[PDB]
Image 1 (cartoon, rainbow, N blue to C red):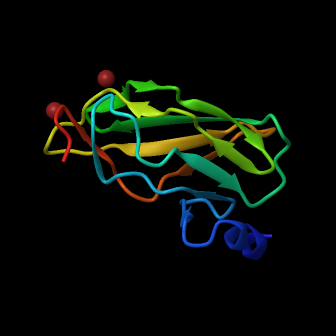
Image 2 (cartoon, protein in one colour):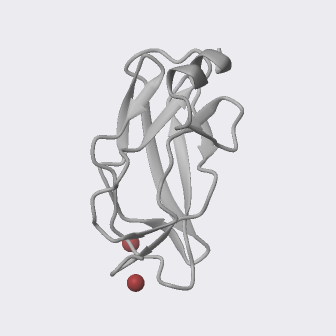
Length: 124
Ligand SMILES: [Br-]
Ligand SMILES: [Br-]
């Protein structure tokens, strides 16, 4: 249940735009190709079988899909932990990216991370 899921990771998970998924917290601004400070996790509140894949993509109005590294993970006990997701493509200092999350249930579900993320060559 959502209460149970929150109680397993208190103070760590945020809403996505889907009622069915939560996520861990990403930086608001990060350096291109730098390892993330908190490994990204997508958390299913609904029934999602172990092994169900989850893929993320980043983009905005001038870059439909910015390069990522290690942008797929598999669900285990309702959590898909990305071991080393990296944001390679840069948004620049003036724009940010939306991160879309696709969970490959049958059929797939799309969610969006709750904040934009800026990616630059130097980072913050
Ligand atoms: Br790119
Ligand atoms: Br840049």
